[PDB]
Amino acid sequence: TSRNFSVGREGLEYVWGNHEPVRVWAQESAPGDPHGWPHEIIIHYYHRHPVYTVIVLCGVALAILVGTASSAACIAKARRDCLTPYALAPNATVPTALAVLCCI
Amino acid sequence: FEHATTVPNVPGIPYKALVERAGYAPLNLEITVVSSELTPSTNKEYVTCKFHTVIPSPQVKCCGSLECKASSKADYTCRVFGGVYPFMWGGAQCFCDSENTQLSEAYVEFAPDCTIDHAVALKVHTAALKVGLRIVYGNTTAHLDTFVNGVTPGSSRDLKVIAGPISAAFSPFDHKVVIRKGLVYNYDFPEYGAMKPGAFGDIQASSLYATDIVARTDIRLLKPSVKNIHVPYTQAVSGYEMWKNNSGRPLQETAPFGCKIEVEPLRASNCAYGHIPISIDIPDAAFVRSSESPTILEVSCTVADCIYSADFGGSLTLQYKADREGHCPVHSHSTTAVLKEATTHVTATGSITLHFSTSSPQANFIVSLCGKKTTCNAECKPPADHIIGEPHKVDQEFQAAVSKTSWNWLLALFGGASSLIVVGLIVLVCSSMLINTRR
Image (tube, rainbow over all chains, first blue to last red; front, side):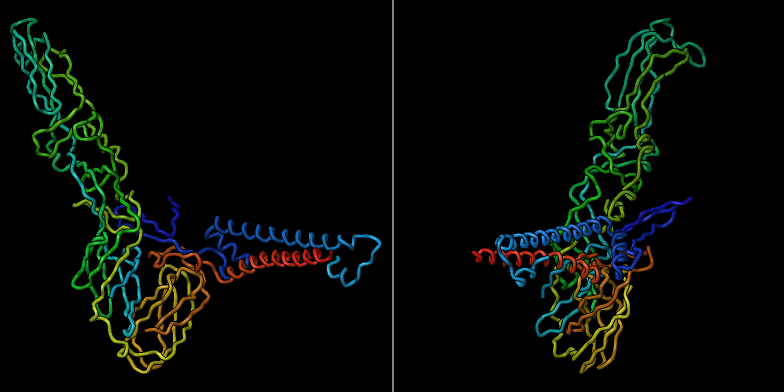
């Protein structure tokens, strides 16, 4: 027959028949390069620490998204409250220098 | 003088530390846990084995009655029957037709072969730890044993080693343990004096040769039916045999941390867990004045290639220049890279190759050759062998466990995500004060 045993970094010891015990420790030979392109980085570190990689990736994605949204909201608010006070006020002309610096 | 260190409790992997004093050449320090023992204080409760019932010859009276007496033998049972009229080879043995009274006895005793096949019940207190080190300093080697308590000065000759308290208190034995033919089982045996028939400890005594055996095996005596003399009886199954059949697996194969259970006295050997805060008092004789030791004018390190494997899967070399010759110590000032050599000869100009090991994908540690710290950096690839037969020599870190490129990617992403918000903030505030000053 054949048996599959999972051995971690701490080690595994098995005794077969009347033989002396032997010990084996697992190395971090995950597939993919931990030193190359980002997708290889991701797959290697996933195969090493799956939950940690998923957590850090969700964290970085949330960090970029929430904060791109913040910058967009800030610039939009600045745009509106900058063109409202007198530029939106009618019967008036707004100079090009003070218009196109943030217009469009 | 005094050095405080924290060596991991792994039996066999060396530990390298560098100790130095002003005006004195640095000295290599090597600590090894050669062997460890975990001896708990034990108290013997009783001794049990497979009982052997003894049925004495019946006593009968032709025309009369008998009264059951009290005896000190284990599980003594007595019964009296009213009419028997017994027979043997030769015919009837009494003249009364119905006034024949028969008395039956049955007690238990240790089987003759119990001197070899017998179990011992034990109670174990707090476990104590004792280790044997192989401290190496200078060009000398010392061996010594000490107790890991924080107060015992276990010293070979003048080492004055004080091993502090263990980081975590762990003991593979529960409160109650059972020993049988060198195999140690974690069992909850019944307390002395309270024996349940058909289970472990149905018969117990303070010693195999004690005369005060006590037992409770649920002996039942029955009314004789056949004509010839007989003592019918029924009894529970031997609880010792039942426990032997349902033993389970021993501590030699259940205990964690790779402990090796052994007996006489009961103990656990070569367990791997926690850390030991040692403290060494090195005699001043070993230390050598800095003026005598050769000095390095310059040193540059270059590393060939590296894999963060458990073994010494790494290489390193360095150029050096010195005004003298002698022996100098080499040390790696990092917690994720350990050298193999402790000292190495030096001859003016030349180059020395040193092997190391690491568990990080960056050989970005500091190497000193009797001083003169130097910076190495390499491109550590992962190893190819999935499985190795040697424990890891360095605990995995985190801050160093991540590659430089991945660190750069995450840093750049977070930096942009933190920069766009602040630039939006500042433009917002400048426009807001502009608008406030508008009117």
